Image: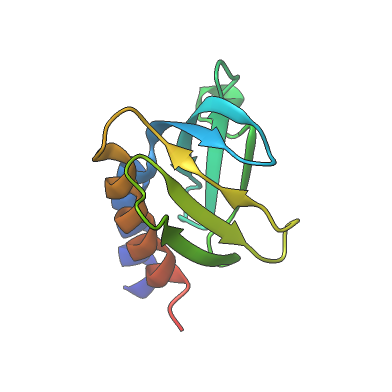
Length: 121
């Protein structure tokens, strides 16, 4: 079932999108915890110490719809830097930066798969 498989599949991506990463942009520069909504419909983050809505994390410190991500890219050298831009919400470009030279890029490719999964063109 296309809905059942998606809802389970987004949960698979959800774990791979649930991470700790430091954002750096016009938004702010802070260490945030990233993740996605239940249907994988959104990308969400928690800035430092947060209050995950009702323990089920229904209260993100920020986020945006996955379908609305206008571009998912990596920097030119992108050693520890990621670059993601969104359309529909106020256009912001999120730089996912982490200590691990792998963690972020794992996120980079994983989000793409999730994005193209539900936002398949």
